Structures are given as structure tokens and as C-alpha cells.
Amino acid sequence: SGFRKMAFPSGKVEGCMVQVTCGTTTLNGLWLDDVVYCPRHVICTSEDMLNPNYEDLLIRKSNHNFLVQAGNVQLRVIGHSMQNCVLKLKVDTANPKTPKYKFVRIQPGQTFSVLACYNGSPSGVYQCAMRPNFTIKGSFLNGSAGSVGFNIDYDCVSFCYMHHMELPTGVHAGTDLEGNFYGPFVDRQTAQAAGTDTTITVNVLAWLYAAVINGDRWFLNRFTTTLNDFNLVAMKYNYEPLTQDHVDILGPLSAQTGIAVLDMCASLKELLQNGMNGRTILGSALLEDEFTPFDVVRQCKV
Amino acid sequence: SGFRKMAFPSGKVEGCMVQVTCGTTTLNGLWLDDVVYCPRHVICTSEDMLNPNYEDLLIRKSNHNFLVQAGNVQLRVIGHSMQNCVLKLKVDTANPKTPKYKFVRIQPGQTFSVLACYNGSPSGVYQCAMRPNFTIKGSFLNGSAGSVGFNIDYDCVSFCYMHHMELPTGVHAGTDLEGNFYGPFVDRQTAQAAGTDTTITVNVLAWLYAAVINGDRWFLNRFTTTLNDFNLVAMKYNYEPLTQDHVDILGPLSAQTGIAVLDMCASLKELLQNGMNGRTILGSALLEDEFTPFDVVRQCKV
């Protein structure tokens, strides 16, 4: 037993990280088959981040202006093309370590692992969620751009995030591997800011089921609620609405614990309105919302 | 910006995990060079749980009774030995993925990355601290014994933990890689209890520094303290003693923030005597003690 924020094993992604350098600017790239993906802001210099004309910057670059190193193996670039807000650098050598993979765009509320990398070298792996306001609360220093987020299912890597930038409140914004940003953000210096964030209700319910599975059940009670009475309280506490589809998705955990979803909602309602009164749930004094139902099922097994 | 529980990249350790089966019992082993290390209770049957005599159980086993599979490769056991609570199975092939490595016995309060594995297949990675009472709070189900904990420094994997068992309170116990158990525990299914745990003071101070680096400053104040006076307060709250060597190890974080270590001690003292008044620090409503000073510098150093 036990329940922990767990990331996926990072080995399959580690062998895909490379360093991309354009002039004096270096960040990380993702080397799959004979293509290296990286944020397009690598082609800027200090006099360019204000209003970059990315189309014109890239045309004026030649293939020999991109220095791609996979460890100490130099990869020769033989084509460069725009992919929305990332670059696809074609190289002459296929990555021998390319895993089975797909590119997937994740929904707010879904989790993934992040391999934080600097200078093409992995530093750490951690788990995090795509927030409802399309940011992630990551841990990233300067040079982390091009670090990727991913899920792994039966040795297939589903890449879902590439890191681009830090917003003024310290949260992080980035794209999918098709180069489209999550949320309204742009890869320019603007006054852009994260919108107000909310709590991921279905995940908090999943985590309370995990707590029940782990023998932590002081917050269960005899009350039940309707879905709508729950959602009115949830709104008041800046929680996302719970849909019928979320209730259905919580079906497997409801069956395993014998606790109906709307009874757990009654528990959550009481926790929102009265607090924990000094108690903890799974070691936490706050309600945790970065575990999905799938994360609980995979970690708690049967 | 941002602060997350961050594990080391797991690739180097993933290539060392194998499956060891004896009869109906399966768990994980660690394959380095031509030796597989695994918990000795793989040789246990139903009648052996309360007081196994492991000398007897091992003599009743031949090299052929041990099935080792690395991926889809059967490894031939050509030798078997018991050292303390682990078994060393000599196999006929050296692991080609053996990383540069060492075996180390970690000290209480130190942290490590755990690669949780079932059937020889890594499932997840997460951070754990060796508690002062020599347990860890992990996430381990049946079949996870032989999962390892490790740190990585300059491509060298320092193995510090092999998982063996779960105590009745739901916390975890295991050995170093020479098979010596952390704490007074024994690998048998008896009523065992850990001592009351204490809080790892140097790590709380490290995390307060992480909070300051990330913009939380509300708990700072002008009071300072002696090391001696603070340690009287720590003793009163079941906090570990702070040594002068802890103070030295916090110096890089005092340097980056401008807060003298004994001033941070004064802040911690006020936090313990008053609580947080519903405020949070780095997102938590509790003081967190599972980050070492090195852990904070790894994520925060400019």
C-alpha cells in the first residue's frame, strides 16, 4: 500500500534528448527517427524576443547554423522547417534509440511526467497536470525549454508537452509536439498572464478514492447529494463542474470501494465547507488534484 | 521557478531490473555485471512466514530452482549465495547495460529515487527520504520487493535501498545492497513496529529556503537564535537536532537568499510555536521534511 506522486520511468525519453544551439542560444531538442523537434525561439537572439518575425528569422538561417549534439555525437542538420511554434530539424541520422511513440494533445486535468533537461542532458523527472487554465505548475530553470512531458503505455511513449516559457506568476506554458500552444499563450514577449485557475474536481474525487483504498476514510459520511447540489457548492469554491462523464469515469473506483460517486461528492462537499479540522488525507493537509482516476487505478492495481 | 518532488532520470537503473522466480514466488532483482541481487525471501513458501530459517530454505534450492528473466531473455543461474538478507545469483552473462555504480548505506534524513517495479518491469519513479525511524513512506504492492532506491552523481548510480516489506502501519522497510536492513526490522511476517518518527530539521530548513527562492517570504522575521537555543525548541517538538555541519550544508542556500541559517532557525521556531494560521508555504499546509539541502540546490541554483 501507500500512494505517491509517481512519474513514468524516463529511460525511453532520455535517449531522445539532444542539445540544439543557434548562435549563442541553446536549449533542448527531442530526436525521433531522423527529426529533431525544438522550440522555434532558439533562432532568436537578445535583440529578437520583442516581436520575432519567426518566418523571416528561419529563412535567413541555413542548416549549418543549427548545432545539434546528442551527447557528444554531432548530428548534421539537412533541413529545417516550421511546425507551428516548434521547429523540425531534419538530420542525416535516425535516432537508434527511438521508442515506439505518438504525439497526443492532452486535455486539462490530465497528468503526465516531465523530464527536465538542460543542455540536452536530463536532470530530473516529475509528475504534473495540465491545469484548467492551460498552464502547468512545473519546476524549470533557464535552459529547460525543449524539455518534454509524456505518458507511457506498454512501452509506447505518448509525448504531450514541450516546454517553452515561464509566465510572470512562475507557472509554465508550452506546446504539444505538433507545436500548438496549450492555452492562449504565444512565444513572444508580451504582458500575457495565466487566467484564473480552478481545482480539478474529478481528480480530487479520485484521490479520495485512493485514500479509501489505502485505509484512510475518516471523511466518509452518511450524506448523499445530487449532482447539481454538489456542483453549486463546487462553483462557490472554484472547483470545476463534475459531469456525468466524470461520474462514469469514477465507476471502477466506486465499484472497488463500494462508495457511490455521489456519496464521495457529499464527502468532498463537507471537506470544502468545514475543512479538515487538523486532519490529513494520504499525508496531505490540503485536497490534492493532480491524480487522475487512471493514475489511482494504475498505482493501486486491484 | 517552481518546486517539485523530483526523482533522478531512471534509465540507467531500468536497464538493470530483472525478474526472479522461485516456485510460485516472483519479485525483482538487480543485474549488475554477472550478478543478480534480490531479496532472500524469494525462496519462501507458505509455511515459512512466521520464522523462516533461511539457511535451511537456501540449502533446499539449486541454481535451476531460480528462474531469472531480463526482458525476454532467460538468464542461466550458474551460482547462488546469501549475504545477510539478499541473494547473489551468479549468471552466465554480464549485463551490457551495467552503469557505473556503487553501493552505499544512506544516512537517516537523506533522500533517494525509487524505481518501483513488478515482474522485472519498471512501473514508476518517485522520491523517498530515509526516515529517522528507518522506514520509508513509499508506494509498494505485492511483487515490488527487489525494487531499488538510488541517487545519481556524474553518471555514477549510487544504489542505497532494496525494498523488502511493508510494516503493519503501511510504511516500508528494506536493506542496503549488502542486505543489511535499515532499522531493527527482519524479513519475516511478525508483529514489528517502528519507533515514533521525528521530523528532519535540516530538511525543513532547506524547504523554507526553497520557499523563499520561490517568492514565499511571509514566515521570515528579525529574530535570530543560537544553535543551542533552537535545539531546545527542536527537542520539544520532536525535531532532530541541528548540527554545525547542517548549518554548513545550508550555506549555499543562505547565500542565494540572503537569510542567515540561524535566522531561518528563528523563523522555524516561530512556525512551530504558532503554526501557519491557514497560510501555505510552497503550496503546503504542513512543514515538509523530505527535501535535503542538495535536493533544493539541484532544483533552484541559478
Image: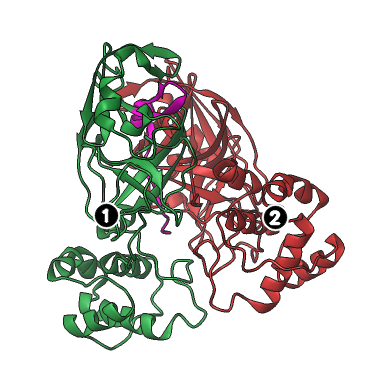
Chain colours: A green, B red
Mark 2 surroundings: few (<14), some (14-19) or many (≥20) residues within 10 A: many
Q: Chain of mark 2?
A: B
- Type of amino acid under label 2: Val
**Looking at the image, residue B80 lies above or below residue A229:** above
Mark 1 surroundings: few (<14), some (14-19) or many (≥20) residues within 10 A: some
**Looking at the image, residue A52 lies above or below residue A297:** above
Q: Tag 2's secondary structure?
A: helix
**Looking at the image, residue B213 lies above or below residue A255:** above
Q: Chain of mark 1?
A: A
Q: Residue at x 17, y 80 (%)?
A: A227
Question: Could you say where residue B256 lies in the image, as x and y percent from the top left?
Answer: 67, 47
Q: Which residues are magenta?
A: A1-29
Q: Where, by quadrant of the figure, is residue A5 drawn?
A: bottom left
**Could one spot residue A260 in this view of the protein?**
no
Question: Could you say where residue B82 lies in the image, as x and y percent from the top left?
Answer: 56, 33
* Front position among marks 2 and 1: 1
Look at mark 1 in the image and give the residue it sits on: A110
Question: Could you say where residue A182 lies in the image, as x and y percent from the top left?
Answer: 26, 49
Q: Residue at x 51, y 59 (%)?
A: B171
Between residue A118 and residue B134, name the one nearer to us: A118
Instruction: Specify the label residue B202 is tagged with.
Output: 2
Between residue B157 and residue A29, name the one nearer to us: A29
Q: Where, by quadrant of the figure, is residue B100 drawn?
A: top right
B103 sits to left or right of B23: right
